[PDB]
Image (cartoon, rainbow, N blue to C red; front, side):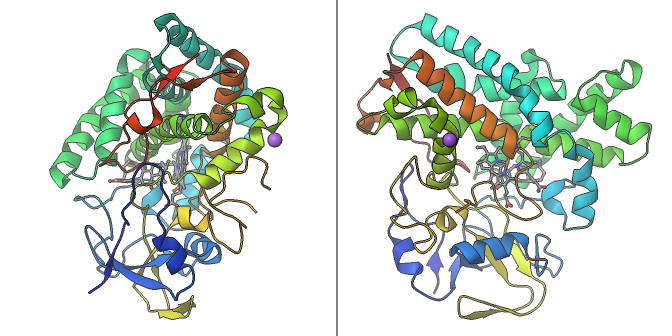
Length: 390
Ligand code: HEM
Ligand SMILES: CC[C@@H]1C[C@@H]2C[C@@H]3[C@H]4C/C=C\C(=O)NCCC[C@@H]5NC(=O)/C(=C(O)/C=C/[C@@H]4C[C@H](O)[C@H]3[C@@H]2[C@H]1C)C5=O
Ligand code: NA
């Protein structure tokens, strides 16, 4: 009988069972759904799973995907493909997410952040940082990039939640798909009649004018970006703020030394266990060795990125949040599926800390920290609410 995964923990806890496993051979676990899998936890092994071509993201051998969600994760977008099919589809978005394009969005990201903090301050201390900033700012940023109007934001929140809830069924997923495809269908029509200079329009051109992708792939790319592109940073904005506010000096190191904000963001990315479960398993495509075990063809290995980011040999005193630490974390993944949004996410999180430190240097929890309400059945770790006071 096998060890169950994911492991017990609450909030942003990193549980001690990892300290035991780092010292042992690769371990097989049973998951909430699908087949058993091995647990890659060493930094080098997680990197291997995510970037070696002997690890496929596609269950091409009849596997039942190891997962935390009742309905298997399947579709026609970026997580459904290996190179080189993956690489050809991504390259349609590629140019829109390089550092040279994303650095152009700093001003806008700050403008929205400032508008969020204006409404939060207007509401009065103590106020929920989740509802006033973590949710609205990242939603606006990607919805404006794509071309979705503010009145429609709530629809994408709903669709993204269904993907990210562990009690979602195949039927729940069929409903999301029908709702979403209808909505994108309207957007595709609108832009065929009236083209626009946004990301929907870019995909509509790539489908219709240059024949680079098909309609199903244009829909899939849109779906991936609007599913991944804002619930992510939302959770992280509140997780990062909560980590800072739980330390005795709170925001003061970054008030005093604003230039260290990019480094803090990186350390927080390394430290925060953002996933409550785990991402896509990969499947070995030939027999290979990993941490003393022969992984046979077809068997699954889960890349545990939170465990990689606390590898005891890569990161001395890995549990310590040291905003000045300086090896590259796996918090945006690695290899082919490394986060297309990574630079946008860095920009959003940097800007948020700039805004928070410049405007509320004495930010503090607005409730006792033991009263913090951490989410329970979500794909990600985070707060239902984050009351802050100034
Ligand atoms: C703090 C915020 C974020 C974190 C921690 C994060 C983390 C990750 C990680 C670890 C993966 C790889 C998962 C795997 O290989 O199994 C990934 C993939 C992806 N992320 Fe991000 N991400 C964030 C924000 C964003 C944003 C802002 C976008 C906006 C477009 C985005 C879009 C995507 C997409 C489309 C993929 C799939 C890439 C591919 O398969 O080619 N993410 N993210
Ligand atoms: C902040 C953490 C980041 C946020 C990112 C959002 C990512 C999740 C969402 C990413 C894409 C998406 O939802 N695209 C549309 C559906 C297509 C297809 N069908 C599914 O049922 C499915 C998933 O169900 C994916 C779950 C991802 C799993 C992945 O692990 C998450 C990333 C996660 C590691 C599919 O991909
Ligand atoms: Na820095």
